[PDB]
Structures are given as structure tokens and as C-alpha cells.
Amino acid sequence: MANSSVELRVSEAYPRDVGRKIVRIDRQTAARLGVEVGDFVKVSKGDRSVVAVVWPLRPDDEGRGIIRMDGYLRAALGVTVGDTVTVEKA
Ligand SMILES: [Zn+2]
Ligand SMILES: [Zn+2]
Ligand SMILES: [Zn+2]
Ligand SMILES: [Zn+2]
Ligand SMILES: [Zn+2]
């Protein structure tokens, strides 16, 4: 079977995550992906992808269907805040 994947809305990084090879998603999404917080995920837009470590979203950001990633990772994928990307176990 293929690994599960989820589409998420691109959101700006928390300030302390800028320049770190980190994306933030919520626990429900990590569970659907079959990963735990702290594992590597692949984030893709079309044929472009990056690999980053999953850190957990803050409580009030859970359930929003978002992924927080800094401008370096957004640029790498050619996406902006408000775009959608796909996330999968790396
Ligand atoms: Zn879709
Ligand atoms: Zn769609
Ligand atoms: Zn593993
Ligand atoms: Zn766009
Ligand atoms: Zn767009």
C-alpha cells in the first residue's frame, strides 16, 4: 500500500521556527500520516518536494488543516501562504 498523504493549507512559520528545517502540523494529521511528531515528512507541490522534521502545532492551531512552514521552504516549493501542499511520511 502507498503511504497515506494529506493536503494542507500553507501558513507562516512561528517566529522561533524560521530558518529551521521544520514544518508544523497537528496531532490528528500526523496520526493519519502514520508518523509521530519529530519524524521526517515529505512536503510536495506538484513535482517539487522538501523533507522536514514534524513539530507540533500549538493547541489553537489544531483542527485548521494547516501546515506552518517558513519562507525558505515555501520558496523551495514555489508556493505562498494560502496555497495547498501535500504531506506524506518521508
Ligand atoms: Zn485535492
Ligand atoms: Zn482538491
Ligand atoms: Zn520512522
Ligand atoms: Zn501559488
Ligand atoms: Zn496560489
Image: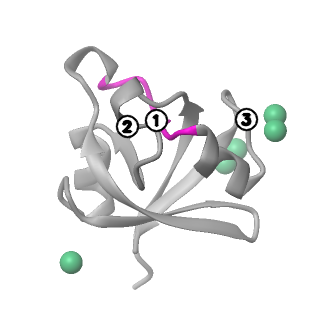
Q: Which amino acid does label 3 sit on?
A: Thr
| Ligand 4 quarter of the rendering | top right
Quarter of the C terminus within the rendering: bottom left
Residue 7 in magenta stretch: no
The picture places residue 6, in percent across and down from the top left corner, at 48, 52
Q: Is residue 15 left or right of residue 86?
A: left
Q: Residue 80 carries which label?
A: 3
Circle 1 residue: 68
Q: Which amino acid does label 1 sit on?
A: Arg
Marks 3/1 in contact by CB < 8 Å: the verdict is: no
For discs 1 and 2, the disc positioned in front in the rendered view: 2
Q: Is mark 3 within 8 Å of ligand 4?
A: yes
Q: Quadrant of residue 11?
A: top right
Q: Is mark 3 on a helix, strand or loop?
A: loop
Circle 2 residue: 17
Task: Give the Cα separation between the discs numbered 1 and 2.
Answer: 9 Å
| Mark 3 crowdedness (10 Å alpha carbons): few <14, some 14-19, many ≥20 | some
Marks 1/2 in contact by CB < 8 Å: the verdict is: yes
Question: Where is 67 relative to 36, above or below?
Answer: above
| Mark 2 crowdedness (10 Å alpha carbons): few <14, some 14-19, many ≥20 | some
Q: Does the residue labelled 1 lie within 8 Å of ligand 4?
A: no
Of the numbered discs 3 and 1, the one sitting upstream in the chain is: 1
The picture places residue 2, in percent across and down from the top left corner, at 44, 81
Q: 55 or 44: which is nearer to us?
A: 55
The picture places residue 17, in percent across and down from the top left corner, at 37, 37
Q: Quadrant of residue 47?
A: bottom right
Task: Give the Cα separation between the discs numbered 3 and 2.
Answer: 17 Å
Quarter of the N terminus within the rendering: bottom left
Residues in magenta, as a range: 62-70
Of the numbered discs 1 and 2, the one sitting upstream in the chain is: 2
Q: Residue 49 carries which label?
A: none
Q: Is residue 14 left or right of residue 78?
A: left
